[PDB]
Structures are given as C-alpha cells and as structure tokens.
Length: 169
Length: 169
Image (tube, rainbow over all chains, first blue to last red; front, side, top):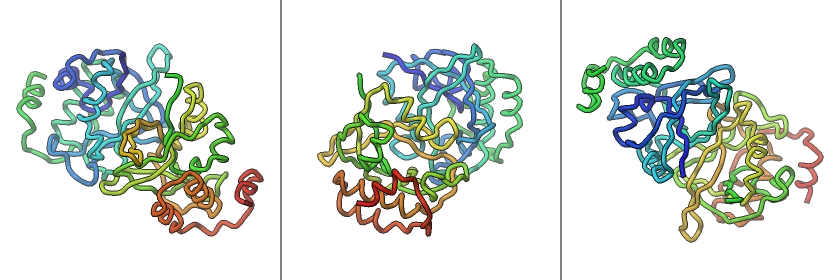
C-alpha cells in the first residue's frame, strides 16, 4: 500500500514536500547513475510559481544525480502526479532504479520533462533545493555542485509560504 | 497482480516482432495517448545497428496524439523488457502513461521514451515493420495513413535474416 518517490528538485526539502504531501516520510538518500541535472521551461513556458527554470533530468552516461527517496501512501499517487503537472504535459512519470549508500538498489517513481528549453533557476528555487540537500545530508561534493549553479536575474518574490521558508533558513 | 500492461508505439506494434523476445505477450487493446507526438532518432547520438536508422520515441506535445497497442505481459517479464530497450545504456527511460481505448476507458501502462537523442529518419525496414503492425492490430485507418506518410532514410543495405523474413510476406 506504499510506494517510493525519488525527489531531486524542490521536494528535497521536508517542509516543502509536506505542504501538499504531509504524510510523506523520509526513506533514504540515493544516487541516480547516468543522469544529468538540468533546469528548464517546459513547453517553452516559464514557471509562474518559481519565475525561472525548474528541475529536470536526462540520461547521460558518466553523470549522476543525487536525491531523497520519500515513502508515500499509494492513495496519494494521483495527488503527487497532479502537483507535477503530468496532464498539462509539464512532466512525465518515470520509474528509476537508484543506489543507496549501503549498496542497495531501490525502485522509485519520479518525474522528468520531455519537451523543454533550458533556462537557469530563480534564486528562490535554487535556495530551496540547496536547503533540502543540506537538511537531508546529500554528499558534500553534490551540495557544492548545487551551490555553483548560476541563477537567473529574477529579483521579484515567490509565494509568501515559500519566502517564509527561505527566511527561517 | 500477476500481470502488467505495456503500451507499444514502434516496432512492437507487430505481433511477430514483439514475440521474438517476448513470446508470452498477449494483445490487450488498441489505445490512444493524448498530448504526445511520435518522432524518430538516434538515442545518445548512436545509430541503431539493428535497424540502421532513427528508432521510435514520443514526447509531450499538447494537441497531438499517438496511437499504439496495449500488450498484457507477466510481471516476471519486467526486467527483460527493460533490457531490450537499453535502459541501462541510456537509450530509453521507463515511463508510466494513461491511454484511452476506443470506448473511452482509461488504462494505466508501462512504456518507454528517449531522453537524450538526435532526430533522424527511420530505415525503410523499420518503417515497414511499424506499418505492418499498425495494420495487423487495427489502429485507426487515418493514423495508419500518418505512419505511411513518414519519410524514411535511404538505407537499402542488409538487415538481420529475422527482420527480412518478416518483411518478405
């Protein structure tokens, strides 16, 4: 009655994933081998939540992506899908096999964009991602990679609830 | 359950082709994937040495559609099907899609698409197999016309004996 979800974008942060998925439970940190992290505008349209490119992954031998595996109730499958804009063509549901630090392979649900234009993330979206990576102890090398991502020059605001999270951090 | 449903849109449209490696696959129904578009390419920049041209993929595109065949397979078959699609070498990723039957019933299916490829026309042999499968398994006649309208590359070399025999009739 449960499934595992591999998050690599803003759902790295516990407080963020809990906004719409309060019952999500931390499972483990894991590595997705032979994928590269990118940021982009799905269907060439900028996210009005985040005001910059949002996270995606594509297959790239030799690259890697680190994330958090969350344990969720299967009753929340449709809700998670809705949040990711699956019907609107923003993301497609994928299945990935990820490696734990104990050398175990875990099968997870995740999401990626299939039609997008690359574009840098807003400062706020980058910050939330870095906050989640730190909170859940992703490898320091990968945290440094995230910190090195060049943001766009958006100087406006995102939602109050998101801005509050950034301030508390 | 003991079984899973698999949505084919490329050479696995043809019963004799899918049965080469998946002999227990059973026809389930014809179905439409809304808001995706069919394309052909060289995944990871590599030209298929089986087909000698671009192979089939799909990507999100509002207003477009892809018709295909839903196959019922045993869950014991999952790992094999993945291996066939070169998931571990980055050729395709596993997706979940929701498709509509010709009676408007929604079905949840496993499928595959490329995440990193260069667009390239299919070989005549690969096109032929796709068109044969579409006709054999009853895809809508207007979709069959779209498949027949695909411009192939100019590959007129040798293909595998198995492919050539299928094509011969």
